[PDB]
Amino acid sequence: HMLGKIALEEAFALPRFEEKTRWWASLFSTDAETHVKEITDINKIRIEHADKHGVGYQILSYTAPGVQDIWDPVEAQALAVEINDYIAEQVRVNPDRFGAFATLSMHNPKEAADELRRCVEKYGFKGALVNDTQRAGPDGDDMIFYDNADWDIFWQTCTELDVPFYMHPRNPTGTIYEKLWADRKWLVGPPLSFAHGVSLHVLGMVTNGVFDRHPKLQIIMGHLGEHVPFDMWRINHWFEDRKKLLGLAETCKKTIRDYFAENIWITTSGHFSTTTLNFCMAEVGSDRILFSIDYPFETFSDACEWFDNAELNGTDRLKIGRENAKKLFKLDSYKDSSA
Amino acid sequence: HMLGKIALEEAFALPRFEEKTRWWASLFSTDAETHVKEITDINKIRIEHADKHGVGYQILSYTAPGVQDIWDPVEAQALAVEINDYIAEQVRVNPDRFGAFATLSMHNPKEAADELRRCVEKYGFKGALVNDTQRAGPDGDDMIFYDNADWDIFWQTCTELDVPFYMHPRNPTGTIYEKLWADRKWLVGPPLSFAHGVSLHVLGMVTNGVFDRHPKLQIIMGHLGEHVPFDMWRINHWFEDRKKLLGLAETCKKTIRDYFAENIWITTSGHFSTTTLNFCMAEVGSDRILFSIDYPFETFSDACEWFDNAELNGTDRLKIGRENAKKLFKLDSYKDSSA
Amino acid sequence: HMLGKIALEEAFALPRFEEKTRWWASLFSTDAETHVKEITDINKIRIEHADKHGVGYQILSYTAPGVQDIWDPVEAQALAVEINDYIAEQVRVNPDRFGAFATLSMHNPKEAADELRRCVEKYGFKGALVNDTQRAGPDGDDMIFYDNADWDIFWQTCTELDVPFYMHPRNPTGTIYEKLWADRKWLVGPPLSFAHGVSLHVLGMVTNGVFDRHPKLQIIMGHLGEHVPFDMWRINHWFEDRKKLLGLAETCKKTIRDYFAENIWITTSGHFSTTTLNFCMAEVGSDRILFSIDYPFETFSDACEWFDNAELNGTDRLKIGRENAKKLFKLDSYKDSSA
Amino acid sequence: HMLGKIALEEAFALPRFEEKTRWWASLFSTDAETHVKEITDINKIRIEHADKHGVGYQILSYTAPGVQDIWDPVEAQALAVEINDYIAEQVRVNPDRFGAFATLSMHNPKEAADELRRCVEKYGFKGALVNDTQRAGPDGDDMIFYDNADWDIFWQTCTELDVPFYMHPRNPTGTIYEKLWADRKWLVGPPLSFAHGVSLHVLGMVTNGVFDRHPKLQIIMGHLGEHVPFDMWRINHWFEDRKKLLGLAETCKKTIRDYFAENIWITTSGHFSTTTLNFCMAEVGSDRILFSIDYPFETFSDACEWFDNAELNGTDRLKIGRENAKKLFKLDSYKDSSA
Ligand SMILES: [Mg+2]
Ligand SMILES: [Mg+2]
Ligand SMILES: [Mg+2]
Ligand SMILES: [Mg+2]
């Protein structure tokens, strides 16, 4: 029904990674052959889906765990560069239907900043999408978080280019996987582990002052905010009425509600629940919520038939379906953008 | 306004642990001296609070991390026995105002089952409250989870005595603390880490078939369910439409919604939000929600002035405030129980 | 998906009233030929719909405006008796699928009480359903309301027989139609006028003390309560904080929330909105909400596909779908009643 | 806590109407002596309240029933002119704290249009506020509605001046009072009758095509929309799926949700319910909701302590508290307008 929707948690994989794609599909897809075809296709199947379901524009990004799974920094950087060059050539076929997020090796702040800049300046990419902490160390068992002063040069590049950063999940690996997840492995991914990682990282950015040093920085979370809106009251209470009397105020200058009004966005990817959407509208505001799908892990039909038919006032259907993202990503036009 | 409310996430500490109590208070209280007095008091300050705020009956339990912090199994068991003997003598002063949950060493399923039985049979305790995984191993860096076949003898003791088990959080320790939390330490506790632990453990019980082998087992989570109701739609979708086509059905026979209708309860402890309560009423049902406070980490005033004044239909105010817990814990009477 | 649902705002018309059926259809149906067949059919089409959509049991009632449109008390009484005899015979064909509400002339309290008693004692009808005020006076321009002492004998008959009374709407007529509705006639019926009538009558019963004189009396409103839940806060405030200080307490002894907890029920007839249902669960409580359809003015498909697929906790889906009505109407087994 | 709030359903009365003020107070106030002082005061008591509760700017309007109670068109017009001249002088004392709505006799479309124009062009009034239908006829028993072609000249004046029209309630009178309300008089006013009138009039404007002929017209309803949001689903269904197939489309060209997105506003006057506000954010959108008080029928304390302390995302608190009204009324700076 609604046309010109924008979706922006929409994944692709390189054709040369078919074995890795099938491993990931063995965890998260019930039809591996269709999954392989859909995650690698850019300009045919993906366009047919969007045409049937009123999706005018999609910002594509690399599948998880992606470059964050690569703990060799030279290999990781070369892979990020390869992916960005590849998707730039692919989306030129349909520029009124596709944009792309930069794919990044996050081993080094300046290296990541330079590649983000190359993507934005050379290819017009719309921002960055990163799958939660970079694997590093001898066997990839270390994690690189971005919520510290070493990453200021990177976050300042984001605000200078004025593009958002999408904190996507990745799977638990190594020591963390063995200790917490191996004995309850069906919880890996969307059921629980994904949100635990993203919420930890983003609230780390909050409590380590990233949005104080970079007040213009825009951060996006999928899956209606990875549990965080559920605890908006509880986090705010334990920040303002407890931890900010014990030292947190030294590195965290605004309330959690301020940061959601000024810096943080949430997306409807993989969470097609009108009851939860309404609750998020109360706790974060319809202005800060964007439609997305999580294709091809979710189907266009599930996401779009939900949203198109959800009971919702017309003002917020427009905002969530396209107008919020249209302003955030400075979209002058695209297919059906004002339909 | 409402009298005879029941609260059941209400903590005490032994007087001999003052140093440990002050360490915990240095993380989670803004007034250490009042905290020490309140967490150790049973029959004076705690009764004065309850009298002012319409709380007829409280089920007391041992402060976190409690016995789960003790990785010496002999020491841990002796401490659990000591705590249960102590609180039994304390609550006999005011039997129409206080019951108690068993405090347990969870190093060994049969040992824990026997001590739960002793508490219920000898002292009339109302169930068990355990602070998420037992520390074990050489330096307490291992975790004992209860979502496996070794714990069947324990869960069968719970269903035979027909008493619930409250899965309370504890702090992250050791390797997990260093890897995920040390660099964002203000998130430890109520802001995030507590819910991550409890939700992992309870959903582990779900996906490892604990409620299939023990369909009468009642499990309680505080803090409006430790994020889980937020993802009810998403978990249900990724169980029924994804993982249960890939192997999860082998150890998980009902839907997540079934388990919340039949086995799982949530509590309002430390989450005094009517907007979130309404959302939980939609996602889990008012029948499955219990009032609680989280005293003395939360104040009676915050919890009770919220609940007493919250906009709510009279049917559900009665149920959540006392009648749900009255039926669950088989309370024939207590102060103001039918006021 | 849910089987054994109960619906109880389901209308029929006498075959000999085809012209009245067609006039009403010309206001409220977009397929008059199907409507005529469906509103007169009891045991074939209506059963086929119920079998397809998991409706085990239906309490049937006479179409609006029905006997309340008849201002000749002799003609009105004879028609009520005719209708009750007719539907008693019809429902005997499928007694495990159908019950009936009494149809009443409400010109005289004792006469109406006697015919309700005959319906319950002779035919086992489940209650009464009445289309708002009884037209009266020489030209049918007066209105008989039931919220006064003259009707105590009638309400005492309801409580003695322990059966509920369903306050259904009727169209505005005569002077009221001319002054308020004739110049905006598209608002007649479900869009506005229906709820204005029923809410006036039920809140009249509240404020004139009917539920104080008859504390066991159960009153049912369709259409999620005819706007009243939206104003529960506002009515409660303007009663307890205003009118109850000015004289209302003389004839109204409990709060509006008390009466919804103790006396008033709402159904989902013609209001297939999960967002509004959730709000009603907050304002009135799931224990007080009953599934219903409003057939043949609404379709089985619209009502049942909505309810069966609505995002709802399993506890409340069971209560609203059938268990609330099973208890209220003291129902024996019926088709799929325990499925 | 929030400063610079805007309220715009704030009433005054002329000093020479003490008897009318006292009769109205005898229906709607529990402290008539304070009410008389507060409803006549402009520049002292009312300012003190606003200073204490963070209300920067108020648009003032004449008390109900006001000029709509006057069925002599000559007396009605003279009184409207008197009131507008009076309040223009009063608000000049504190022009950074007060604006005014036009008070109008609505006996004649051209006359009302001319007085609205005088108010805007001579005094800079912000719009019009009218208490539902104009009493008319020899004994005041007729009602003038504005949802017809005779009023096109008036609505065209609203859009030409680009100012909104606030449809405020009035009490039921004459035959309507006798037939519907006299025997249940405690429902008169906020409990029920007020909303019945306004919702009828506004939905009449919808279904008689006023917003089709005048697509720029902005209409404001108090009291969270006078029940209409509760039935948004039901009205929309009975328009688009029923009446629009039977002839309504001839005079009503968009959906009810379109008109709430494009033409209709609601305020929080006299409805200090976060639960209902959240529901209204789902059904109408936070962009279309305005803070207001309904002083002196409601207190500043009730309205502002509710709103300032309600659990709400920061984006919508800002919009509802002041930014929506700042844009709608094109307001220059006022006290704390950017605080
Ligand atoms: Mg994704
Ligand atoms: Mg606790
Ligand atoms: Mg009906
Ligand atoms: Mg007013």
Image (cartoon, coloured by chain):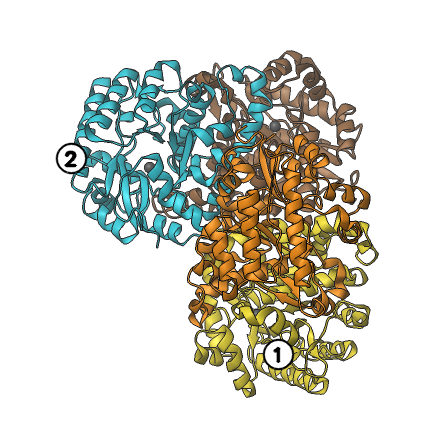
Chain colours: A yellow, B orange, C cyan, D brown
The residue drawn where x is 43% and y is 35% is: C225
Query: Which residue shows up at 73% across the image and 63% down it?
Result: A204
* Ligand 1 within 8 Å, label 1 CB: no
Left or right of C317 on screen, residue A210: right
Query: Which quadrant contains ligand 1?
Result: bottom right
The percent position of residue B271, horizontal first and vertical second, equals 64, 47
Q: Are marks 2 and 1 in contact (CB under 8 Å)?
A: no
Q: Residue furthest top?
A: D19
Chain ID, mark 2: C
Judge whether B155 appears above or below D210 on screen: below
Disc 2 is placed on an element classified as: helix
Q: Quadrant of the C terminus of chain B?
A: top right
On whether disc 2 and disc 1 are found on a single subunit, the reply is no
Q: Is residue B189 visible?
A: yes
What x and y, as percent, mark residue C86?
17, 32
Q: Residues within 10 Å of mark 1 (few under 14, many from 20)?
A: many
Residue bearing mark 1: A66
Instruction: Looking at the picture, tell me which residue is in the foreground, B13 or D14.
Output: B13
Along the horizontal axis of the image, is B36 left or right of B291? right
Q: Is residue C105 left or right of residue B297?
A: left
The chain that hosts pointer 1 is: A
Q: Secondary structure at mark 1?
A: helix
Residue C113: where, in percent of width, then height? 28, 20
Residue at 66% across, 66% down: B136
Q: Is mark 2 within 8 Å of ligand 3?
A: no
- Give amino acid for label 1: Gly
Residue B262: image location, x then y, percent: 45, 51
Residue where numbered disc 2 is placed: C89
Q: Amino acid at mark 2?
A: Glu
Q: CA distance from mark 2 to mark 1?
A: 71 Å
* Position above or below: D35 against C84: above
Q: Where the N terminus of chain B falls, by quadrant?
A: top right
